[PDB]
Amino acid sequence: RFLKVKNWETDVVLTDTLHLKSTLETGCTEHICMGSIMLPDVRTKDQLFPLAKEFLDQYYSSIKRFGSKAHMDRLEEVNKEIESTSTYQLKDTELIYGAKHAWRNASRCVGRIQWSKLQVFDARDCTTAHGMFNYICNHVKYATNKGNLRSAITIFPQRTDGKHDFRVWNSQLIRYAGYKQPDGSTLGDPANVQFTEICIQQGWKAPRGRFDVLPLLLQANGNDPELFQIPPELVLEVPIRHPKFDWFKDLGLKWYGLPAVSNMLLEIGGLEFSACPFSGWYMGTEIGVRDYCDNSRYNILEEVAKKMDLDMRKTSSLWKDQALVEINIAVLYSFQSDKVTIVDHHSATESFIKHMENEYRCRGGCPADWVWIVPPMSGSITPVFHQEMLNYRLTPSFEYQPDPWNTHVW
Amino acid sequence: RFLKVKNWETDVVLTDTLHLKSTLETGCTEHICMGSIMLPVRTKDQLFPLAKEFLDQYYSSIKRFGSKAHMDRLEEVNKEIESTSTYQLKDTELIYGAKHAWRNASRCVGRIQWSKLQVFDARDCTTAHGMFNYICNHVKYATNKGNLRSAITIFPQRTDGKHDFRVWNSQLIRYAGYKQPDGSTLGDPANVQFTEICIQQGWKAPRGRFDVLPLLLQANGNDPELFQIPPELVLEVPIRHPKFDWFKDLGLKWYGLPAVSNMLLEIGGLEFSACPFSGWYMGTEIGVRDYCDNSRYNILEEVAKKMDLDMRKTSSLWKDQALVEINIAVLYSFQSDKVTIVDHHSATESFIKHMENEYRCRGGCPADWVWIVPPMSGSITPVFHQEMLNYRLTPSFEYQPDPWNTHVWKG
Ligand code: HEM
Ligand code: HEM
Ligand SMILES: Cc1cc(N)nc2cc(-c3ccc(OCC4CCC4)c(CN)c3)ccc12
Ligand SMILES: Cc1cc(N)nc2cc(-c3ccc(OCC4CCC4)c(CN)c3)ccc12
Ligand SMILES: C[C@H](O)[C@H](O)[C@H]1CNc2nc(N)[nH]c(=O)c2N1
Ligand SMILES: C[C@H](O)[C@H](O)[C@H]1CNc2nc(N)[nH]c(=O)c2N1
Ligand SMILES: [Zn+2]
């Protein structure tokens, strides 16, 4: 039960002992593997104290003060505060550590070599949706940094009794609207049709274009959410052109520079932060492969292949594959030309292998979800394809949570 | 207890009850998923329940469960076990078992074909020369002048584990690999260790880049013996590109018949350690893995050079561009020579239809996403978006150690 992982391209073998510290469950059993399943009332006083203890133990071990006066003192202080208030508050030092380690533990994230360079914005003093809007504009501007992107998270007040949740209703701070057409097709991003309508069916007036930046729908302290438009000068966008095909410009494609996931839940020492938007920078395939070429998304392969004059009669001409490469060359070329941070899938997966070897050496392992880490194109020519990975759940963590409109006591 | 899988591109939801008939373990637990791990002497004691379970499944499939034929067969197998410690399958049971091992192979994307399998019964074989003869006939039948036909040849089952039949080749047709004193490799690097064994056993190696390996065959636990497959039985395809005339000058070719020969077939608790099986190629097996793996022929650089791509920064995606061209060439060459092949778009779409059909008629279809998704252009194939459940059903194909690590040499 001191497990080994092999890289089959290089024969490097790493021994994982970190998994023995895993706490939550994977969804698999000895009889069935659920590795490809996408998604496999508050804490009571009894549940919360062990969770705090485990977190504080690892925090004080990380600062080389395990079993110290200050350590035992903090355990006592939090234990007293839980007994008293039925919750507790993290010191700023513990909050920053917990957020950095939530990212470090995110087994589906290929970008984790950067995990220790996260800018943490403490927004626990926030009380209103206007205040949330202010914190998010500041996040967006800080992270965008005129195209030299910097990783950041903004942490809003923690769940109390679940009636007073802070939530960002958008799935990302910056996404494009989706409108179902009269005839039956979809204009804009189909993934956002429901949210685009909860915006319209709540106040928003839509340009009804192909790339309309959605408004923010912000919920403070459990109240009804409020619409806010992000200042357009804070939303950095990149028009997509190709370094060889002059007609690529005519396709009319753009994308935004800042990937900022806003719908997840951050868990630190048993406390729950239901509103914790975080951002980094894009790996090129997220836009070029998934956003543009998924059939349930912008689905542009047909149109691009036609402009390339490829033989689309048979699938064995690999015209889809050929167009796919060109689309992704253009995405990287456009971001690079406009000096907006982006990473290609070869560079990012190579970095993740180096990160894995760092984590195995200095931590005893690194939880990793191969199904998500392997890029959605050219899988086996990236080094992570040949890398065995162990997947398990460590805390602090980012977790999924239900969409708030299915839950909101309106 | 029922289980749901969702296709996130179509929202089709399927319900799995077949996983309840799974017995063998996956390697995973509630606390760790080993879904990407490559790899995660039997007594009369455990054998009759394994036999009974198989025979119950067999007689159910033929709508004779509980019949007198069913009960007599159980009785007969039971008494054959206690008196001889093993038993023999009827021909009907062998064919059923082999087809169902393929049906149950969760890493196989080609399973829509599972019921069209030609089963060759080689259980009367006794010598390596006899094995060579059976294998040649399999190769000729399966190749069918380029119109490939799925087939499996089944040699005698394990008895005491000291008399195993084994094919020491990992596939019936493979190219040799030679390590040079300067550290480079000539031929297929995956086959260096096996090539060295063949040479040690007396094979005269041509020492070229595409030398078909000899067969190394072990009957009845004896030392293995070398045989050369008749060259006229080995169908090969020279690789050229439909637009790039310089591509032929890379000197590439491949063989048409993929025939895996190192796995173990388990049926009713019986173990067939020599059971070579063959189908036809999915293009990416050759064009992505065999040609472009860094540890294989590794032709990306020279192809990208001749294409004159920007090779100075990986963000030109020169590797991705060359990879598509190589895979176009593989498909074009096989089709032009009229040798059966399937592209990864067709094969993944067939597998989705197969999988849905299996959920309807069978209650499930065990599938290993990590292996089913093709190694290029993953998310533009429909299997990428398909949730899958992986579990172990018998009859099954299993891995077994390479024979040279376990064989006791007679000398
Ligand atoms: C800075 C560069 C980063 C890159 C290139 C990157 C890359 C990625 C990619 C490609 C995915 C798969 C996403 C998808 O397919 O939708 C992912 C998932 C994820 N990323 Fe990262 N990311 C970065 C930064 C961050 C940061 C700063 C955080 C949080 C502080 C984070 C947390 C996550 C999480 C939680 C997931 C899903 C993991 C899970 O459910 O286990 N990432 N990332
Ligand atoms: C007829 C066309 C077939 C195609 C296109 C096909 C395709 C494939 C592919 C692409 C793989 C992944 C292997 C790799 O990447 O190296 C695979 C695995 C496999 N195939 Fe098929 N195959 C076919 C027929 C067969 C037949 C006839 C059998 C046996 C009777 C078979 C049994 C298997 C098994 C046992 C595996 C490994 C599965 C596991 O460990 O669960 N296949 N196949
Ligand atoms: C900071 C960051 C940077 C980046 N470049 N990319 C990122 C991608 C995600 C991400 C997006 C969508 C996801 O999928 C959600 C659906 C699957 C179930 C609901 C997940 C999965 N956790 C993660 C999160 C953060 C990212
Ligand atoms: C009939 C057939 C046709 C085809 N087109 N392709 C086929 C591929 C395999 C196959 C190839 C390589 C494998 O990998 C070996 C590694 C696992 C341990 C070492 C496995 C393993 N399950 C199966 C087996 C049969 C195939
Ligand atoms: C069904 C399957 O789990 C689903 O398509 C997953 C596969 N791998 C993925 N990998 C990444 N990085 N992102 C995804 O959205 C998905 N989707
Ligand atoms: C580490 C990883 O499990 C290993 O590289 C697997 C990944 N998926 C694969 N899928 C197929 N079809 N064939 C393979 O050899 C592999 N190798
Ligand atoms: Zn698993």
Image (cartoon, coloured by chain):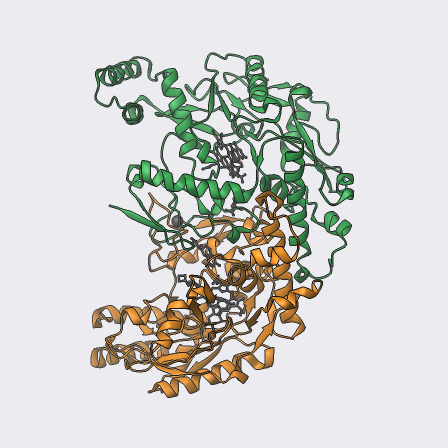
Chain colours: A orange, B green
The answer to whether B179 appears left or right of A162 in the picture is: right
Near-viewer residue (B142 or A159): B142
Quadrant containing the C terminus of chain A in the rendered view: bottom left
Q: Where is residue A379 in the image (x, y as percent from the top left)?
A: 56, 51
Q: Where is residue B296 in the image (x, y as percent from the top left)?
A: 65, 42
Residue A391's place in the image compared with A198, above or below, is above
Corner quadrant of residue B344:
top right
The answer to whether A87 appears left or right of B388 in the picture is: left
- How many labels sit on residues? 0
Near-viewer residue (A329 or A26): A329
Furthest residue toward front = A183
Q: Position of residue A362 (x, y in %)?
A: 51, 63
The answer to whether B397 appears left or right of B64 in the picture is: right
Near-viewer residue (B188 or A193): A193
Residue A393's place in the image compared with A41, above or below, is above
Query: Is residue B364 visible from the viewing direction of this image?
Result: no
Corner quadrant of residue A190:
bottom left
Corner quadrant of residue B236:
top right
Q: Position of residue A192 (x, y in %)?
A: 42, 68
